[PDB]
């Protein structure tokens, strides 16, 4: 029994942990399957991808091509249908017709063995025809056989009759494959489209209150949902909605002691009022939450709840399950940390005294919110809990409810980021906020749209309550516009945290990435009506970007992405394609200065010849342009961050 | 059950074909086992490699270290012992003693949590003692426990008592590892030293004849063996020793028609006088071959025979086993080809009619020569026979005779070259002859000494009967000296083909890599005694290089190799280390002009600090130098091709 088969097919990709975990896709997503394929000797090889659905049903004929000369690396694009666990193989084979044609094209004009060459061709086309059904196609090939055998015609005429486009056409659909050799199957987990594609909006319900009751309730926060839906968002991410501890409650601006009216951090979960399966009393009741969920759903919005596996000192778990915490010799539980940050208001969970009880309680809590319509969870700091714990929990939840989506908020080292995605997190936060130059963006997106896409789906939040980047602090509104265009067009999933659209960019202090007067620690009423009337919000641009994504399939996927060269370091250009849809984006990364540049398009990567001209429409403005291999652009910050163009027919 | 364990241990390397083929080593060879290891949170992890022999016996405690900050990539060096099939795993674990010592070193000097931190250490060392079998080792740790708890003693002294050498010694032999998590075993094939290390010499017995009988015999050719052994070679590689066909026999200089006394190519195997298991009548008998092998062995020389699975048209297989060839419709067999080259004198074997018969006959032929003392086979053009055919044949032969070494003469594309090594070829020919500039040599040797070394062992033939490189053609003797130094010091296995040491360098024509009057097609009598009297041979340099290799373990391994920067493109510098042996080589790649350069040594890669001395002896001259971090060299072609230095201790 040999490891290599008759025709080598080696190192099939995508592959995750050597085949022990599934590669990822969503319904309708196209991705490349590749392999190393070659044979002994100099005859031609062919290959094809066999994609099988959860019932074992194979997909269409999907022939492969060598991706670059002399590499023996072959690839083809496949497309996932329904959700479930699929599998794929690569089949490799001797290609006798290509081999014979190449030898006949030489030997016939040279007059070498022409009788043998033509008869071998005749026998070979007969062999091909034996497998073709449909009298017409088989007749086509058999007529080429008879022409090859017709010694009353010149040798070149007999040969030419085997090389007509009509014959190529039959052979294209019904190729003759020798020595077919298959790779072993690899697993593919196909999930619902929202796992890859969607626009996210994060806000704090308690901040959306009234003049007379500043602390919002679920009923007053529900009134914010129409504006969010109107900006074209699909997912609403809420910080924790549970009671908040009082012991070591944090005050405003991340101070260590709260005054009497201070609301504390929502992540300091738990009190005598309840824990992770309960509602903060000032938000109202579970029925109020159901109202919020209902109103969201009527607007096409899905709720994502924060799941933060940790506790305030007042949480019932502290006395109900002491073994879920690490106690020092004096009984104290050290407060959680994520250095250099400190979380004085919470205890971290310890997992090694009662891992079964913790997994049971975790999936209980998730299934409670799932029963109330929550099918997406944003998991807070997953990298401070064991990787295998999430592996278990996610497998459990998705085993009964495969539609549930888990988003990993893991801003940490690459190994942990990648492993969390690989053990089942449907989506991952990314380094996006720290990729701001053209070089950083090009390199990072080349990584994310490449091999990493077989196990990770990025969620590009342009800001979070914890990340106000210096780019936004120093660039003002034109920088907010640039980052929104970049996030919305470079990832099929993007998000903003409320106040982004108002261009809030005052840091806690120079060199910080915290917001001054952060909403994590205080109510943050925002005058949405005034900002809208005065035009001091970028909500219209956000709306337009989400509309462009909804109208352009190229922007609803990740892996098809190509950067085109420009001659200015501050101007980046890239395109994305899905079927006949092509989107071409040119962004001025400079938020302070007008930039002119020549964008030299790689015409073939747009499916075009070098001399063609591409008619494009700038979906941000509706202006039409005529663009060829080389195009002058002039982008004035404030007036326009970018061109977001579709190529027209 | 989860794929990831409690402490993640991921992507263990080396790995070949995802673990379905073994990684390679030889007895006494060191190599690095690496893994991605981390945990949740910020406490310290530890890791170790468990290498198990063919009986499953674990090797010594082999702790790993993180290889670069923030990468979570860990490594440790292991050393292979006796031949056979070994395995290795990586274990990872929480390291509570390291974690506590780091905390205590910060807290105790600041007087923070002193009683609590000291008590944490006390009960931890008590935990470590629980598993210590020896009464005196337990009493050692309990001594530190008692000092840690001694409240009548200064806090600094309580801590210091936990950090003594006596304590460390107990914990090095019984470390406290928490949450120990293991990878699944990976296979390692350990083979005899000659698989990795050896000097090879190829010659044609038929050329070593007499004026009365120009065609040498095994009895006359045996007279070359003293000179070959005196040059310090270990392996004699013979072209095929079988009868040679007459039908379509090639003439001199690869012409298509032999005339009269023409001897033909030895690779055109087979006649009515016998096939692959027979001796050419002009070479003598099987008994004469036995005499040759015996006389070789008495001189410390092993015989490698050429195995060329192909037939002259006169080979008995052509009519006994017609199904071992591809036939055209008139029943004729096309001659073999390897574009752009043509082999009009032979038929290629076909493998798809009777693969079992071909495997059976192949291993029968190999076992015949094995019974006559041939334990090494040079396999001609393996890439024109199926990869899985060699996989099966090599596993069959090595299953009964694991000492047999197979060398793949596959000058082809990278995937096939890599795959042949991976399915079992002990050694591979390489791109060496076509790597002649400093950039070329540095990049290629970086590849060969890096990940390729887990599956392939290079044999650097500086020439072969088919490869006379333009570098040698244009450079003359200084070029032969350079390529010998390079081949001998960059690979633990190197070789030359007879006449290399005479600096034979006349090509068939401008732009060809064939030799004029190639020995493949004619007897080539050489007056060896006269060349040595006239000093036109570099046999003294070849002899010296082989002695240097035999005296310096650093040159008998592959993976430890470092290139040091110089400030002239034509001057390359590199070092190799094995234990306390260090070899430092500086080569002038320019065969025409003297070159002056400053060599700037990466002292840490030598095991030295930047201020230290590098006393070296140039083993080519016996000269001594006092080198340092920056050394001026001057190398004159024809006089000093290189410095080949050992570092003195
Ligand atoms: N990476 C996330 C992790 C945490 C920790 O749960 C959250 O931190 C917030 O919540 C803590 C507990 O109440 C406060 O101590 C911090 O001051 C405040 O920033 C945020 O989601 C985000 O930083
Ligand atoms: N890569 C090796 C392959 C072959 C083929 O076996 C050998 O080629 C020699 O043998 C042929 C058959 O006799 C002749 O046709 C060629 O002219 C002569 O070069 C050499 O070992 C080497 O080229």
Image: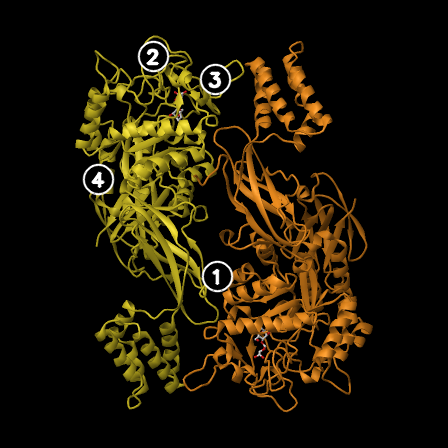
Chain colours: A orange, B yellow
Q: Is residue A383 left or right of residue B100?
A: right
Circle 3 SS class: loop
Q: Which residue is mark 4?
A: B547
Res. A211 in view: yes
Dot 3 or dot 2, earlier in sequence: 2
Binning the other alpha carbons within 10 Å of mark 3 as few (below 14), some (14 to 19) or many (20 upward) gives some
Q: Nearer the viewer, mark 3 or mark 2?
A: 3
Separation (CA) of disc 3 from disc 2: 24 Å
**Residue A351, x across and y down, in percent:** 48, 73
For residue B333, the mark is 3
Dot 4 or dot 3, earlier in sequence: 3
Circle 2 SS class: loop
Binning the other alpha carbons within 10 Å of mark 4 as few (below 14), some (14 to 19) or many (20 upward) gives some
For residue B262, the mark is 2
Circle 4 SS class: helix
Same chain check for tags 2 and 1: yes
Same chain check for tags 1 and 3: yes
Q: Nearer the viewer, mark 4 or mark 3?
A: 3
Determine whether label 2 and label 4 are within 8 Å by CB.
no
Q: Residue at x 38, y 34 (%)?
A: B393
Same chain check for tags 2 and 4: yes
Determine whether label 2 and label 1 are within 8 Å by CB.
no
């Amino acid at each position: 029994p040999t490891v290599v088969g008759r025709i080598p097919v080696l190192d099939v990709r995508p592959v995750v942990q050597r085949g022990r975990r599934p590669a990822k896709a969503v319904t309708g997503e196209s991705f490349e399957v590749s392999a190393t394929v070659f044979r002994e000797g100099h005859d031609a090889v062919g290959a094809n991808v066999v994609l099988r659905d959860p019932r074992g049903r194979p997909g269409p004929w999907t022939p492969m091509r060598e991706l670059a000369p002399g590499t023996d690396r072959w690839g083809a694009t496949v497309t996932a249908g329904e959700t479930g666990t699929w599998s794929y193989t690569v089949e490799a084979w001797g290609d006798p017709v290509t081999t014979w044609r190449h030898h006949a094209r030489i030997k016939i004009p040279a007059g070498l063995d022409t009788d043998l060459v033509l008869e071998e061709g005749a026998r070979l086309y007969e062999r091909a025809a034996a497998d073709v059904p449909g009298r017409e196609d088989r007749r086509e090939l058999l007529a080429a056989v008879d022409a090859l055998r017709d010694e009353s015609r010149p040798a070149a005429s007999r040969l030419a009759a085997a090389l007509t486009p009509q014959v190529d056409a039959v052979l294209a659909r019904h190729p003759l494959r020798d020595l077919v050799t298959s790779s072993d199957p690899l697993p593919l987990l196909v999930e619902r489209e929202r796992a890859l594609y969607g626009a996210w909006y994060e806000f704090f319900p308690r901040s959306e209150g009234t003049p007379h009751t500043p602390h919002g309730t679920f009923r007053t926060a529900a009134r914010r949902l129409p504006a969010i839906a109107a900006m074209g968002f699909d997912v609403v991410y809420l910080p924790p909605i549970h009671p908040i501890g009082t012991t070591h409650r944090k005050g405003r601006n991340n101070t260590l002691s709260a005054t009497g009216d201070d609301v504390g951090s929502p992540w300091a979960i738990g009190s005598p009022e309840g824990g992770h399966d309960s509602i903060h009393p000032a938000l109202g009741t579970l029925d109020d939450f159901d109202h919020f969920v209902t109103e969201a759903g009527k607007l096409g919005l899905e709720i994502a709840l924060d799941f933060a596996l940790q506790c305030s000192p007042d949480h019932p778990w502290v006395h109900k399950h002491p073994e879920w915490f690490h106690h020092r010799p004096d009984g104290t539980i050290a407060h959680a940390e994520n250095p250099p940050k400190k979380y004085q208001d919470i205890y971290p969970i310890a997992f090694d005294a009662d891992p079964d009880g913790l997994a049971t309680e975790t999936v209980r809590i998730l299934r409670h919110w799932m029963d109330h319509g929550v099918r997406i969870f944003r998991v807070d700091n997953p990298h401070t809990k064991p990787v295998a714990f999430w592996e278990r929990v996610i497998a459990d939840i998705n085993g009964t409810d495969p539609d549930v989506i888990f988003l990993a908020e893991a801003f940490t080292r690459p190994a942990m980021m990648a492993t969390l995605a690989q053990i089942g997190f449907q989506q991952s936060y990314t380094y996006f906020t720290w990729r701001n130059t053209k070089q950083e963006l090009t390199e990072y997106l080349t990584e994310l749209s490449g091999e990493a896409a077989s196990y990770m789906r990025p969620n590009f939040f342009a800001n979070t309550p914890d990340i106000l980047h210096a780019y936004l602090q120093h660039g003002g509104r034109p920088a907010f516009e640039v980052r929104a265009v970049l996030a919305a067009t470079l990832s099929p999933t993007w998000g903003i945290y409320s106040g982004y659209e108002l261009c809030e960019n005052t840091p806690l202090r120079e060199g910080s990435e915290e917001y001054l007067d952060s909403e994590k620690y205080q109510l943050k009423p925002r005058d949405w009506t005034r900002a809208a009337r005065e035009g001091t919000t970028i909500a219209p641009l956000v709306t337009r970007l989400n509309t462009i994504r909804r109208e352009n399939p190229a922007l609803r996927q990740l892996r098809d992405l190509h950067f085109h060269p420009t001659d200015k370091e501050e101007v980046i250009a890239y395109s994305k394609r899905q079927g006949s849809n092509t989107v071409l984006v040119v962004v001025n990364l400079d938020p302070r200065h007008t930039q002119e540049a020549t964008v030299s398009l790689d015409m073939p990567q747009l499916g075009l010849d070098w001399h063609e001209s591409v008619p494009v429409r700038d979906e941000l403005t509706g202006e039409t342009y005529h663009w060829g291999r080389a195009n002058y652009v002039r982008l004035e910050p404030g007036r326009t961050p970018a061109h977001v163009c579709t190529v027209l027919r």
